Picture 1 (cartoon, rainbow, N blue to C red):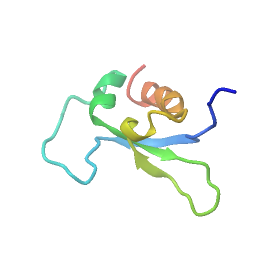
Picture 2: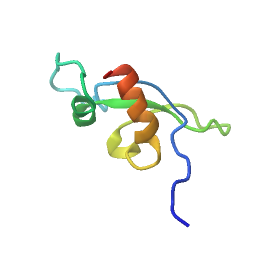
Picture 3: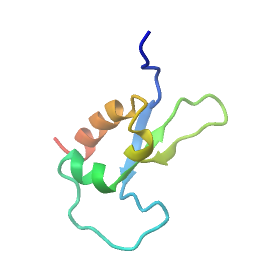
Picture 4: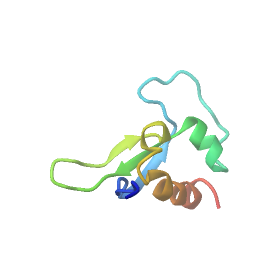
Length: 81
């Protein structure tokens, strides 16, 4: 019995991983998944059980729950092609 339980339902959107920290700007946009994967966050629509709502996580926190899969198709449908 491996481990692949669901985790990310939908990537509502994304943006620079400011994490309320901010400090410098980057006009390099996001061509591939590295630019983002190296400095970007993503609104993760998690399972809407009742009190849980979309949130803005980052691969450093959603890179291990099936998110990268839906997040990968999101970065390619929104940050790459």
